[PDB]
Amino acid sequence: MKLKSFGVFGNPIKHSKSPLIHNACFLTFQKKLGFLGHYRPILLPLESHIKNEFLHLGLSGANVTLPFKERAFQVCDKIKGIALECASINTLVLENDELVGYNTDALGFYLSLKHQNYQNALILGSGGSAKALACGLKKQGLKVSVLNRSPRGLDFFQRLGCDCFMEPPKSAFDLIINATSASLNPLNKEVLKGYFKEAKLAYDLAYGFLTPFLALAKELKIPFQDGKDMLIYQASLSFEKFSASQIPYSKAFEVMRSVF
Ligand SMILES: O=C(O)C1=C[C@@H](O)[C@@H](O)[C@H](O)C1
């Protein structure tokens, strides 16, 4: 039976658990799919082109992670769904010898919840991961405030029409976040401390261990959440696509939940 190759592009990449959850699905659904899928971590030079290399390795699909999501958006041949208004894609597909981009962090992060009760939120960090979040919450009608001491391309949220800050809003929020090329190892403990209190939900993109960020977070007897549930939702959605839509996301989501 056919070996179809896939992977997650990134740098760094060794800690990604995408291979675990996608391979659970390829094995589970090969009868329905009619090929053997194999998903693998691909560590990418920062200087390289995802496009040239996706074809070099003859992938059929792939995810994109830090820091290639916007670089990725550029080199598609076609871009579909919410991606058009995200300027970042996390999912690639060869369809008809055409490279097609999607973005699943959006919906992914959204489905990450669960009960449709919320009005606004505050996004620390100015990355592709946050771009799709913002844009994702707007669509789900929210009052979205971004905050990053970084500035360039912070216009995106501006052009998109949400409130941009380089100083914590003397305000009170239902969701705080973080999507920083920092965290390795955010914003000063105090500016943080004050905001965190009377927040409705905490939430960190990152998964694996407990981050400085959340480590504290929970400590303050707060409702919390980490990247796990999102990782799975956005993967199941990318899988649906990988399956050229033969496998529904939510079926994938069950298989994936039950290994990780
Ligand atoms: O760690 C991972 O494998 C991933 C993380 C997120 O950025 C996702 O958007 C990406 O598709 C996969």
Image: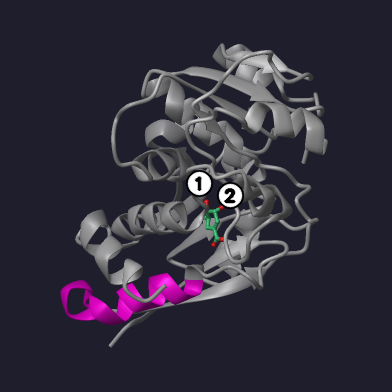
User: Which residue is outermost to the front?
Assistant: 221
* Labels 2 and 1 touching (C-beta < 8 A): yes
Q: Residues within 10 Å of mark 2 (few under 14, many from 20)?
A: some
In this view, which residue lies farthest toward the left? 32
Q: Quadrant of ligand 1?
A: bottom right
Q: In which quadrant will I find the N terminus?
A: bottom left
Q: In which quarter of the image is the C terminus?
A: bottom left
Q: Residue 23 appears at what percent x and percent y?
A: 39, 77
| Badge number at residue 224 | 1
Mark 2 vs ligand 1: CB below 8 Å: no
Q: Closer to the N terminus: mark 2 or mark 1?
A: 2
Residue toward you, 193 or 136: 193
State whether residue 74 appears in this view. Answer: no
Three-letter amino acid code at the position of disc 1: Phe
In magenta segment, residue 255: no
Q: How many labels does the image show?
A: 2
Residue 224 is left or right of residue 128, and the answer is left
Give the percent coordinates (x, y) of residue 220.
61, 43
Magenta region: 19-34
Give how far across and how far down residue 226 sits, in percent: 52, 53
Say which of 23 and 169 sits in front. 169
Q: Name the residue under label 2.
A: 218
Secondary structure, mark 1, is: loop
On whether residue 30 falls in the magenta region, the answer is: yes
In the depicted structure, whether residue 84 falls above or below residue 43:
above
Image: 21 above or below 127: below
Q: What residue type is labelled 2?
A: Lys
Query: Who's the residue at 23% across and 75% down the image?
Result: 29
